[PDB]
Amino acid sequence: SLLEFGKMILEETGKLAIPSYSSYGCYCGWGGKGTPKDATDRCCFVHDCCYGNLPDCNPKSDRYKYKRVNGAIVCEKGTSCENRICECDKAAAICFRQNLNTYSKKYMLYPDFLCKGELKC
Amino acid sequence: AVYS
C-alpha cells in the first residue's frame, strides 16, 4: 500500500513521498501521459508499468510486509499480489535513491499541458 | 498518504 511505499521512500531518500514525489514531472503521482522528464520521473514511469503488470492486484490498498537486512529491502512472504507489489515498490525506492543527485525542484507540481509525447511500458 |  501507499503506506508501506511512503515509508520506504522516506527511509531510502530521506524525502517525504508527499510532497516530493506525489506531483513530480509527468509520472510521479496521479499522472500517466507523455515523455518522462528526467531519471526520477523515469523511475515513476517504470513503477506505473510495474503496477500495470498486475491487473487483479490493488496497489494502493493492499498491505505487504518488508524488513531491512543491513539496509537491503527484503519483501516478506504474503499473497502473490502482495509479493509482486512489494517488488515494484522496492525497485522504485532504489531507483529514487540512485537518482537523488539529479532530483530538481523545477519538476515539482509540474503542469499537465507540458506532459507531451508518448511512451509504451 | 497518497502518491497516487
Image (cartoon, rainbow, N blue to C red):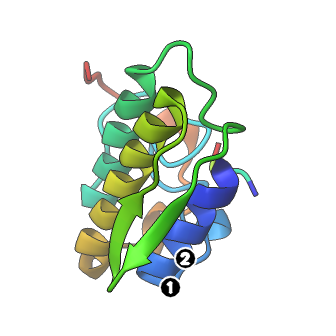
Q: Can you see residue A19? A: yes
Host chain of mark 1: A
Look at mark 2 in the image and give the residue it sits on.
A10
Residue at the image point whose x is 50% and y is 61% from the top:
A66
> Does the CB distance between marks 1 and 2 fall below 8 Å?
yes
- The quarter of the displayed image where residue A119 is located: top left
Look at mark 1 in the image and give the residue it sits on.
A14
Residues at marks 1 and 2 on the same chain: yes
Q: Nearer the viewer, residue A47 or A76?
A: A76
Q: Nearer the viewer, residue A114 or A62?
A: A62
Residue at the image point whose x is 36% and y is 29% from the top:
A49
Label 1: element kind: loop
* Image location of residue A67, percent across then percent down: 47, 69
Mark 2 Cα within 10 Å, few/some/many (few <14, many 20+)? some
Label 2: element kind: helix
Residue at the image point whose x is 62% and y is 58% from the top:
A4
Left or right of A8, for residue A75: left
- The residues tagged by marks 1 and 2 sit, at their Cα atoms, a distance apart of 5 Å
* Image location of residue A72, percent across then percent down: 31, 74
